[PDB]
Amino acid sequence: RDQSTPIIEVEGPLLSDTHVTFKLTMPSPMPEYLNVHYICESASRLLFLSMHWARSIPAFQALGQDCNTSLVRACWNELFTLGLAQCAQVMSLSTILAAVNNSRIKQVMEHIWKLQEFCNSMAKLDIDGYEYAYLKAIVLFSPDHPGLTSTSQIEKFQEAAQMELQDYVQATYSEDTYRLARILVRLPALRLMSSNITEELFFTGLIGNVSIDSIIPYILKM
Amino acid sequence: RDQSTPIIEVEGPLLSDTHVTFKLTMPSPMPEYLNVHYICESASRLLFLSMHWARSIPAFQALGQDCNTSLVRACWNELFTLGLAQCAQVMSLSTILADRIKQVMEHIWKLQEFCNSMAKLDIDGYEYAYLKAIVLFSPDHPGLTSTSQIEKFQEAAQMELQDYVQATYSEDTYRLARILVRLPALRLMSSNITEELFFTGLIGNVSIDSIIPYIL
């Protein structure tokens, strides 16, 4: 009913001003040709670019490293996939490899399916850069995942994010009222997709063996 | 886009703009005694009601019959959990003591916080029913048939739920959003643990993903 100091006796859950700033930008450059196993590096650029976008949020750094590192550890795959559809301009990854080679109903197909279908849905809805920046925001500041240390602070961020995201849709797309809701009903799809299947498929090269989850903390350093 | 006939002969009609008030009645008739393994019964009492609620809805049956027993079989946990935020029951959540890592706890937590947050938001009317529609008619799920038609239903429920909120409120204009950003939680809990926790007192091994087709 009245939280100026969180469950603990250190922080102070302070309300918001203006959440996300100019983060609406997200470029993703890439070097040379043909489909070897540089894929790992491609997904890395996104993965990396994703960690920074989030670490750059004036309300994210407030949570402190201990809380940040954990939050991100709880949704990197949602962010990665959100951005996947947003930068899907590259992905020609028909990485459906058919299974030592002397003189097993693994459903990785479903995951790839859901993945394509989600990108597609978001394309069909023509989600713009702004909505993406906020959609990622609503995802990042989820009070659902267990193991989070912020109390109502995180809650107060998701509130603003969805708040500020209703406003942008409210104006920018006045011909469509049921659009916002149409966008929010996409978020559940991000949870249906397994983080592991996503890791096995993209990150295998170098980052693949080390467990992206353990590397997260260092990616948040620089 | 442009979709009026699937990739065959059949077709997809647009919303009839309706889902009768009978889709608001969720009274779970519970037992009488103390807390034995009757939690499995209350669980079933809710499961069977939940599944029977989704079948009352016309758009459901119209969606063929195979597709029916495929869609619900793909979200039952979500519905049961949604409807589980309807504690006309007691403290069945004391599921205590158990070599294990006991991840179960974490699950009880999620289900706990969810029921809390749902209650904190006061789900006025049975927006639950409409949220159960958004859940029921999810195109996300694999192995689904009339995908496009389901989208039409889910799209319907999306609009109606909206027209019920901003038309039944003023002070909270950001409600719709708020109540929508809750759905993802539902996909954050495993059905396995749910089945393993509540329906842990049924005839031997029978998995819920089996008894589903047996609808009356």
Image (cartoon, coloured by chain):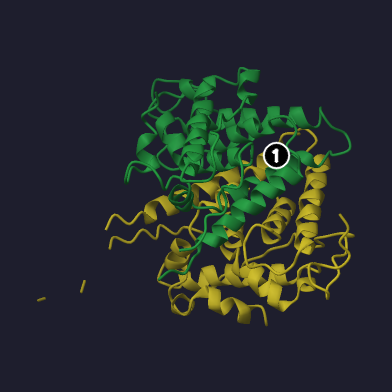
Chain colours: A yellow, B green
SS at badge 1: helix
Identified at 86% across, 69% down, the residue is: A12
Q: Position of residue B49 (x, y in %)?
A: 51, 30
Query: Is A148 placed above or below A124 here?
Result: below
Q: Is residue B68 visible?
A: yes
Q: Residue furthest front?
A: B33
Query: Is A108 placed above or below B168 here?
Result: below
Q: Position of residue B154 (x, y in %)?
A: 59, 32
Query: Is A75 placed above or below A41 here?
Result: above
Nearer the observer, A164 or B90: B90
Q: Quadrant of the N terminus of chain A?
A: bottom right
Tell me which corner region of the image, top left, top right, bottom left or bottom right, holds residue A13. bottom right
Residue matched to label 1: A181
Q: Quadrant of the C terminus of chain A?
A: bottom right
Query: Is A11 placed above or below A129 here?
Result: below
Nearer the observer, B40 or A64: B40
Identified at 61% across, 17% down, the residue is: B16
Q: Residues within 10 Å of mark 1 (few under 14, many from 20)?
A: many
Q: Position of residue B66 (x, y in %)?
A: 37, 28
Please give left or right for residue B78 compared with residue A98 in the image.
Answer: right
Nearer the observer, A82 or B153: B153
Please give left or right for residue A35 compared with residue A66 in the image.
Answer: left
Q: Amino acid at mark 1?
A: Ala
Tell me which corner region of the image, top left, top right, bottom left or bottom right, holds residue A71. bottom right
Please give left or right for residue B42 compared with residue B22 in the image.
Answer: left
